[PDB]
Amino acid sequence: EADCGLRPLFEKKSLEDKTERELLESYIDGRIVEGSDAEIGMSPWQVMLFRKSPQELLCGASLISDRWVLTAAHCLLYPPWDKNFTENDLLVRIGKHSRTRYERNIEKISMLEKIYIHPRYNWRENLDRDIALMKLKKPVAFSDYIHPVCLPDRETAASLLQAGYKGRVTGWGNLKETWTAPSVLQVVNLPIVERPVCKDSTRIRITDNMFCAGYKPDEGKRGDACEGDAGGPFVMKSPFNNRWYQMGIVSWGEGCDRDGKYGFYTHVFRLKKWIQKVIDQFGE
């Protein structure tokens, strides 16, 4: 997608959001609060996935072109809970900022024509290959508020996804919502964690198709990975072309009863073969 990742209200107006520079420099400040309300149109690829009946927020997702939305598989299909949502059970809401209000002349509601779950999705064990695509019934018209994120290529994947570098999760806290057993869009900047520390920190068997971001419980940081929505976008800005790239999809978070624990994310580039195939073969 030629114009992907350049936000109409920032990169296009040559404006910078409050914390993108810290992201570009991988800068870790001594400050404790690392999460805040999102500025208007800071994350315009942000999608809400809704159950039609009863109406309710199921998951996050992201816009990757006028016809395609990306999310996590376990948002749509999860047999242990008898979860199998059809195209006909769901709506997507794009261009939103506040959760608890319909936002006319800003947001757009689309129907789904078809769902594509990764064939090797593994719910039995660890949510390996936790990825799905949703083809919109109708192409959606872009605005200042609705704009697709880029997907990484080989070189972008290689430079950007390294332990120590900093990405960004946006969402309305649905990872918190599901498990405690806040209405404006949240942004949190989180660093990518070394693989052995991700391995060490969780009980799940992690695979190379996953990465984790967040802070050691050492530093008192209260920038939370659970501000994410399951299915939602983990993004990073390239210092080479000024574009936003979706490097991750929120799969789960650890200690969403406030712990300062890592979020786990589907490694998008690693599954790009499947993504491209459905987009190329089953699209236009």
Image: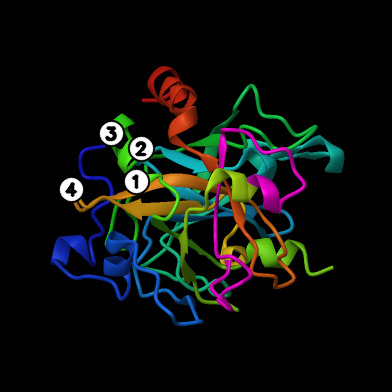
Residue receiving disc 3: 155
Residue 273 visible in the displayed image: yes
User: Could you tell me the amino acid type at mark 4?
Assistant: Asn
Quadrant in which the C terminus appears: top left
Residue 194, percent across and down?
52, 48
Q: Closer to the camera, 102 or 57?
A: 57
Q: Nearer the viewer, mark 2 or mark 4?
A: 2
Q: Are circles 3 and 1 on residues that touch, CB within 8 Å?
A: no
Residue 220, percent across and down?
59, 79
- Residue extent of the magenta highlight: 199-224
Quadrant in which the N terminus appears: top left
Is residue 209 found inside the magenta-colored segment of the image?
Answer: yes
CA gap between label 2 and label 4 equals 14 Å
Residue receiving disc 2: 157
On the image, which quarter does residue 8 sit in?
Answer: bottom left
Residue 241 is marked as 4
Element under disc 4? loop
Name which residue lies at 57% across and 33% down: 208
User: Could you tell me the amino acid type at mark 2?
Assistant: Ala
Would residue 192 appear left or right of 24 to someone viewing this image?
right
